[PDB]
Image (tube, coloured by chain):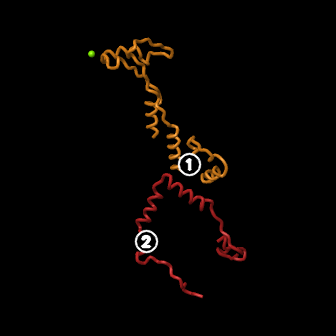
Chain colours: A orange, B red
Amino acid sequence: NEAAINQAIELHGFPQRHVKVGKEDGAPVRDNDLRRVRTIFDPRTTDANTAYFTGQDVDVETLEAHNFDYSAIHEMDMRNLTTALGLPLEAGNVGADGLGSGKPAELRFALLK
Amino acid sequence: ASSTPQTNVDSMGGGNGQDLTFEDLRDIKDVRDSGGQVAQLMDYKALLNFGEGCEIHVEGDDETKQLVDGEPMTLSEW
Ligand SMILES: [Mg+2]
């Protein structure tokens, strides 16, 4: 699950630029044409305050960072592993509501001791 | 007013030992051996019931005092 989260963050945690070229139902654009457009829009050499000027038949679409709750997956994984190893949840740098207080706290720390 | 108890006790004689097979018993071991969350909870039950340790008492222990290994012990010491 840890490896899955790292790979998922790498692909989905960051938005990515999608330049679409040519008019819809218009003239087709070939690889050698896209090489020249790639040279103009290259993220390697772009900077924060670059601006773009185009004809109407160039679209700078984007892949959004597609939201997923990796924090909750980490909390679930850590809860699984700590409980399997007989440690309290708190040992894994993860916590839970109510369980940090009162008789709920007293029981789990009694079990540990 | 009974020496042998006169009330019967629902013995499953038609079941030969008992309804518990060794396979049922060994399946309890399979759950215990498996680790993960369910085995951990039943280990917590054992620790709550029996993990805080024990003390032996004898009522009137001092009156038991006797020379055992040629030296005094009460029954609680023994
Ligand atoms: Mg054509």
Circle on res. A57? none
Residue A80 lies, in percent from the top left, at 50, 47
In this view, the residue in front, A84 or B11, is B11
Report the chain holding disc 2: B
Q: Residue furthest front?
A: A25
Residue A32 lies, in percent from the top left, at 31, 15
Please check whether the numbered discs 2 and 1 fall on a single chain. no
Residue at the spot x=65%, y=66% of the render? B55
Report the chain holding disc 1: A
Q: Which residue is mark 2?
A: B19
Badge count = 2
- Residue A2 placement, left or right of A96: left
Q: Nearer the viewer, mark 2 or mark 1?
A: 2
Give the answer, above or below, for where B27 lies relative to A97: below
Q: Quadrant of residue A55?
A: top left
Circle 1: element type: loop
Residue at the spot x=39%, y=16% of the render? A58
Residue at the spot x=50%, y=55% of the render? B38
Residue B73 lies, in percent from the top left, at 68, 73
Give the answer, above or below, for where A83 lies relative to A93: below
Q: Quadrant of residue A23?
A: top left
Q: Which residue is mark 1?
A: A87
Q: Quadrant of ligand 1?
A: top left
Give the answer, above or below, for where B22 lies relative to A7: below
- Residue A41 placement, left or right of B1: left
